[PDB]
Amino acid sequence: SFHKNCELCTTAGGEILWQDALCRVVHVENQDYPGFCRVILNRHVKEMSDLRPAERDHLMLVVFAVEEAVREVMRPDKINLASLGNMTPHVHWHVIPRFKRDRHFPNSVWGETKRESLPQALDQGSTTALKKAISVRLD
Amino acid sequence: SFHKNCELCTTAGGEILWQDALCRVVHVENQDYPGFCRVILNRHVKEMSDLRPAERDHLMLVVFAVEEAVREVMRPDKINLASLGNMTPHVHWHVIPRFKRDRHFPNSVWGETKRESLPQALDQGSTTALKKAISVRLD
Ligand SMILES: [Cl-]
Ligand SMILES: [Cl-]
Ligand SMILES: [Zn+2]
Ligand SMILES: [Zn+2]
């Protein structure tokens, strides 16, 4: 339910862009990846296959709506999606806009750094646009 | 449709465990990660959101079946799920069984190694057990 020592039970995880009963979407303020968002399950569950099929589905619909919003607002070269949870075993999806000359490309963002990069952190305008784009698709 | 220079248009990608029209499930032979499976879309498509919602849904069903089968056969500490495609932009999902004693834990498998880990490659019984577990769920 709620583990008092799990950061995703105890913290928002970033600026909340959208939420419902099942989950929340946040902009993670990552200096190397503006527009990096996470879909975080509200309750503490370890694996996607711990969820009932209907919950799995609802969660994945939010993830794909967030992919679409990030594509539209950020216009990235590639989208990466991942649910890892090795350090924090509480279901959460990274939705990451990648660019050919970003810090790590074509490595994953968890891999070796490839180049210097200096992407402009999101402005209120972009953050707003992300919120609108997610809302359009989910509300 | 078919990109002649794309590894996932021109190779099985591993030993095939299950397939239908839309996709195939393979066991990736990775000496550090027995039970690493991949769900590869059969045609060339760059992003998940480039798929029709009926196709996204079905692919994700296959992914979640493979997750459940890997958990049953491998009894991992954690599952990692990921669609990256930075090096090969053809939709495919990594379904990775992780263990506390694996090479990278709690890093992602793309990160720095933390320990020695020389695991036993899967026997015919385990690979066959994966095929059966996947098939029972999808057929
Ligand atoms: Cl993670
Ligand atoms: Cl990849
Ligand atoms: Zn938690
Ligand atoms: Zn291809």
Image (cartoon, coloured by chain):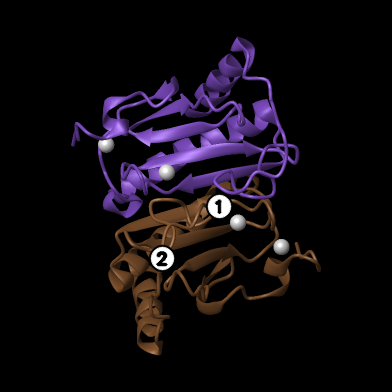
Chain colours: A brown, B purple
Badge 1 crowding class, 10 Å Cα cut-off, few under 14, some 14 to 19, many 20 or more, is many
Q: Cβ(mark 1) to ligand 1 < 8 Å?
A: yes
At mark 1, the secondary structure is strand
Task: Find residue A59 and name its label.
Answer: none
In the rendered image, the vertical position of residue A119 relative to residue A89, given as above or below: below
Q: Residue B89 appears at what percent x and percent y?
A: 31, 45
Q: Amino acid at mark 1?
A: Ser
Residue identifier under label 2: A66
Q: Quadrant of the C terminus of chain A?
A: bottom left
Q: Where does residue A103 sit, x and y in percent of width and height?
A: 43, 63
Q: Can you name the residue that lies furthest to the bottom here? A: A124
Circle 2: residue type? Val
Q: Residue at x 54, y 72 (%)?
A: A20
Image depth: mark 2 or mark 1 in front: 1
Name the N-terminal-most of marks 2 and 1. 2
Q: Secondary structure at mark 2?
A: helix
Q: CA distance from mark 2 to mark 1?
A: 14 Å
